[PDB]
Image (cartoon, helix red, strand yellow):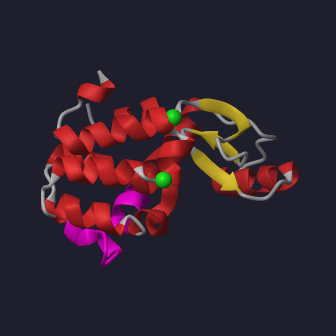
Amino acid sequence: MNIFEMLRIDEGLRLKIYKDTEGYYTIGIGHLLTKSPSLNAAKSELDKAIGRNCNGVITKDEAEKLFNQDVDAAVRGILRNAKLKPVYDSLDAVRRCALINMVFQMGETGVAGFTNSLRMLQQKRWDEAAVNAAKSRWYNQTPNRAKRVITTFRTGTWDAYK
Ligand SMILES: [Cl-]
Ligand SMILES: [Cl-]
């Protein structure tokens, strides 16, 4: 298991524009296109992302390209954020993947708001971190996914994805 496979499991793969859990236009492997309720807008942003007139549909290849860009961007975002970096560098490989997942889902800012859990993770207080993180809108809104990521932080293993 790696970051790609993990996110591919949590986000799925859809070749046509669809709405995510929050109702936002998305495509591919969890690639948010726009928060706007306008489908046209979504179509616009998609073409601009791909570089061609897609008419709301892309190929697998194209979905994977977006995914590579998105993961790269997520990691780079972590390293550039003064609140996230230290945490990330303190972790082992597996747990780092859990942190990337959260950032991919919620954005850096969103993750950066988990102050207390981040501190706990930095202190390697696994269980405490797991219980604090569950007290969130994130956990209540997408609990199965959140449970998988939380378990990952908790154990440092991929058991939740097997
Ligand atoms: Cl809560
Ligand atoms: Cl979920």
- Say which residue appears at 28% left-offset and 47% top-offset: 130
Identify whether 2 is placed above or below 113: above
Image coords of residue 125 (percent x, y): 15, 55
Question: Which quadrant holds the N terminus?
Answer: top left
What is the tally of numbered marks visible in this picture?
A: 0
Q: Quadrant of the C terminus?
A: top left
Q: Nearer the viewer, residue 159 or 67?
A: 159
User: Where residue 107 sits: x, y (%)?
Assistant: 49, 61
The answer to whether residue 3 is visible is no
Residue 93 appears left or right of 84: left
Is 85 one of the magenta-colored residues? Answer: yes
Check if residue 2 falls in the magenta segment: no
Q: Going by the picture, which residue comes out furthest to the bottom?
A: 82
Write down the quadrant of residue 117 in the picture: bottom left
Name the residue rendered at 17%, 63% in the picture: 122
Image quadrant in which you'd find residue 57: top right
Q: Main secondary structure of the magenta part?
A: helix
The reply, left or right, for residue 75 in relation to residue 9 is: left
Point out residue 103 in the picture as x, y percentages from the top left corner. Answer: 42, 57
Residue 128 visible in the displayed image: yes
The residue closer to the viewer here, 110 or 59, is 110
Work out whether residue 5 or residue 119 is closer to the camera in this orientation and state it: 119
Residue at horizontal 73%, vertical 57%?
45
Percent x, y for residue 41? 82, 56
Report whether 3 appears left or right of 140: left
Looking at the rendering, the stretch of residues picked out in magenta corresponds to 72-88
13 with respect to 72 (left or right): right
Q: Quadrant of residue 58?
A: top right
Which residue is at the front of the view, 77 or 118? 118
